[PDB]
Image 1: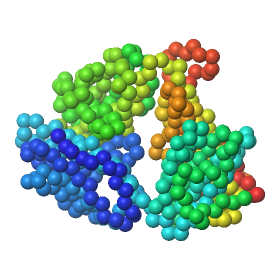
Image 2: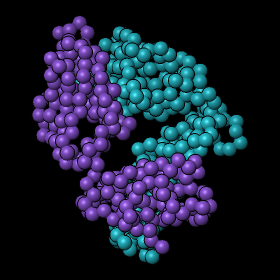
Image 3: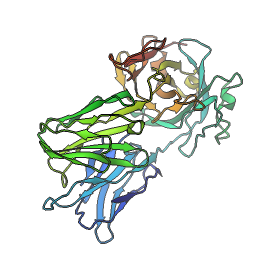
Image 4: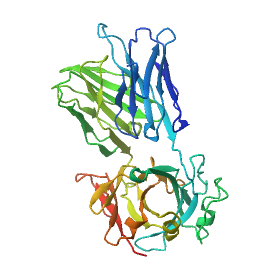
Length: 197
Length: 243
């Protein structure tokens, strides 16, 4: 049996992160880390000592496993699973996985320009959405907790060839009183947020 | 380097109707294993097979059986699916039961429903960039919304001039419920694609938000008035604008 904290652990890009697990079985002698993106299949990361930005370590006396990620990047954001088993000289040595820790690395937004823009449907309908965008990663987007208004959480996109990342969230509603002006009233947003006319 | 495949990758079934999910690997590995993954519980092993004609219960076998007639395959069989078997299943293979790399398949998402009345494909709409964003930033963000679908079995992608794009995209990691006040709320999911103003401005550029929905199969019986919610793609599109 393996104990692992679920997180999520949120850190700023460039920070060192430490992920760890504790186990109770002294026959465990092989220790690896797996990384799982979104809902995709886990894939081995470390089974080692150091590997570039990664160092895996084990203290068998403390029964404590750790993975350190130096200079962390938004692309490290994933679930990390510690895996372990006995030796192959053992009668049974089935690999087991801890239940994973979710890591979010917050992108460093170098020039925030928070704004709420209204976008209209391409097809027509009187339908529109409200896009809050370009805010720094300190910003939290709240679910407004009104049943007829829908608000996504923040999501970071990367325009690789501009060396530009930006956060955004989307809100929409059918309530006749809904307007981009009020859409994110349930969140704390920068006073300088731009509401075009 | 090769791989583990699972079939199907998505499946809806009514309670009590038998189904099997295949897992196959072409590496001649002796050891294969089935797990489920559920929120809060991580991977839990259902059953494992050390070699051809050798199978063994794992930690959560109830409701499942397997077989291992050949090295290539290790199917998971649910004789009488129950709702709490709704889950994400992963097959894995390795040269041996441990102290060695396990290779995982891509996952099979299974939803087991009381009936199929609440299954619905997405509707899809593309919202065009704000002229205010273009003038303020010299960039242009399109938003796609997929709405009304259930269960949450979708894959959203963007296609610019007929080719898939990944740069400048981000899609919500999970949908939200549209009518969380009702049972079996249909779901909505949003994604953004951001391009330069120059690129959006060209009327020859064509942008499509494509949602693959995995729904009922040919064989599933359908008796509601509306079109059967089969596996299908639903898209919406926008062209660039000089504006």
